[PDB]
Image (spheres, rainbow, N blue to C red):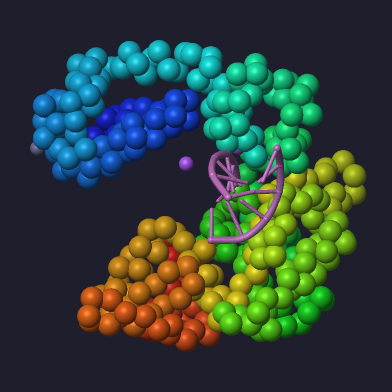
Length: 327
DNA sequence: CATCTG
DNA sequence: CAGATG
Ligand code: NA
Ligand code: NA
Ligand SMILES: [Zn+2]
């Protein structure tokens, strides 16, 4: 956690780059289990040969660890941090809609900057365009003070459209957090579930509402169950407009909301633990359901849930207010 | 995983 | 349809 930190981090830069710049998914994958195990390891790696002793710990990586242990740095790492072609891809990639693949293509087309981007707005698709257009706002964190205002609206509109709608803002926002990076709404309706053959209007009617009153600004992607968008809290009394925020809305069959809601609320660490305990208690949990474990090895059959409560109960645990769902 | 592009 | 992004 700090005894093998540098090692783990270097491996991290390394792994990362393999994947992003080079295409080296193997290599890339290599660095990763390696950092992973070194990460676990209870001692102070004092040499490469010592490391080597580990699994995922090959010869090359050991070598690397040596030079790093030997001297406060790594040549290769130094060589990669410089290289404009590398840095380019790390940067282009910051654009919502641009991934590595794309970051590569452009650079080899010579697009390497924001400007470049604008100049070539013809070459980007819709998401990418939006991504570019709001590059700044998009990197800005979201203060819970705004979150509540947001949340405030979404909920009232969902309401007006149908009293029966069920909306929930999950996320860290949900677990307490002072700021969040995006608004994530879990949505369901009685009239929608596991068997119930579809109902797209279910998701599309609210989307519409939100754009109605202009809360929703743009559409990143709009499917029948998940919508990727952009929103914004009406600029008050003109002088202070708000940043454009990323936002997601997703329809859930009523018969699987809470596992969802639970799941989406995190934290990753809380899940796992919760997950592991369910397992003890003779169960299984995932994003959609909780099932009683047969002994034959495994086994299914969806336990029935009406709240986050029903879940804990199942695994017979202390209900946790979201705030304390940290770890 | 669900959506988009081409 | 494969392949990309979030
Ligand atoms: Na991006
Ligand atoms: Na292939
Ligand atoms: Zn020791």
